[PDB]
Amino acid sequence: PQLSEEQAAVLRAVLKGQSIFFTGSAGTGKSYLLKRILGSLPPTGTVATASTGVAACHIGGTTLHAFAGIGSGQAPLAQCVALAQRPGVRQGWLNCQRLVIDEISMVEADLFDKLEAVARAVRQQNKPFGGIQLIICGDFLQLPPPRFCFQSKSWKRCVPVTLELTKVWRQADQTFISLLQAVRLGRCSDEVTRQLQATASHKVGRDGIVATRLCTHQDDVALTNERRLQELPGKVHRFEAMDSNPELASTLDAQCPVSQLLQLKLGAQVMLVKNLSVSRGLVNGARGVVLPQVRFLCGVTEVIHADRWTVQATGGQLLSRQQLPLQLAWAMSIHKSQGMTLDCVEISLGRVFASGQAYVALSRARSLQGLRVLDFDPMAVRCDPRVLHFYATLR
Ligand SMILES: Nc1ncnc2c1ncn2[C@@H]1O[C@H](COP(=O)(O)OP(=O)(O)O)[C@@H](O)[C@H]1O
Ligand code: ALF
Image (tube, rainbow, N blue to C red; front, side):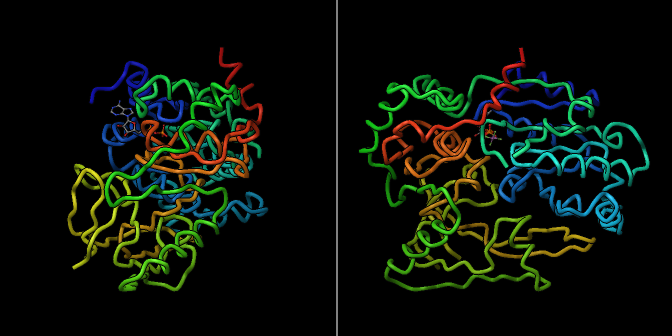
């Protein structure tokens, strides 16, 4: 699939060597562009960062928290930069010349400046960002973190030239497309409440697949995913294989998407993966076992295997977990649901409020039939922060 003109504008400018921030509608094409950029930019200098576990596996690796070798905190630059200045953190900090980032919406502001001086102090250069080709990407109308990074003082002073993307590539029908922006900008008519309310009835989930529901908080999804599991009668089959070399919670927590324990039963809904398939990106599925041999849509069932999820712990050092790429569907968490293109989802709008959670949830659904909104979006669902002002001064 050839790139749009809007996209290829970004490609050439990063190839030029310029720090370039570009933003885009949910499904603008943003994160696919970095797939071409990372293929375009040359190993040895590129780091492939992001702000969640799930954002880094879509792209390359490393989750900012991890790569920087720090975890925000009230440690001034001093401890931070000294914590930045151990081996693995340094050696990796020094060699990079182009630092891609993704899902910048989530990174707090203070993290940026603290990350900022840290980048300079290690490299010793007093260029804007330690003189890194600093690529950035994300949409601030999706999930917040307060104080997004553009409020940070390093921002703009890093000299990023702001670019924009349009023509949403994920949803084909303009009727659905026009919907999200109405929600995105925080504007709800009935023709922004009734198209969906109408839909609530839908049946979603082709064959054996079920609607992967989305939730406001992480705990419900932990419970709701599992309650369904114990309910399903059959072989427990909870093999897992948390084969982590140390005994550290953080590696399987932040910096990778894994749970140490994968209680995969006989027929519960297994969703997501690690891409690396011509026909299977990150879609939900289930089937019989012999080695899960899981069937998702597309009608493609093959045998699934566990791999390596390399991580850099804080203060240097590398821990790695070796678990299966799959995770339990049934109810995906919404904050973990950025950077996702989900064919079939279902969400309850009514108690799910936060400058974005509305937008972010539905927008991750290709076509309207997949989206299984529930409780009427009686306005209030669509809340907004007035960050639109920043996108508004983008004359
Ligand atoms: N230039 C392009 N060529 C092919 N597919 C694209 C392009 N731009 C966007 N897409 C589609 O958009 C999806 C990725 O959406 P993306 O913009 O990365 O999500 P988000 O905007 O939420 O980060 C992919 O499935 C891909 O097929
Ligand atoms: F803006 Al995105 F996944 F990068 F919705």
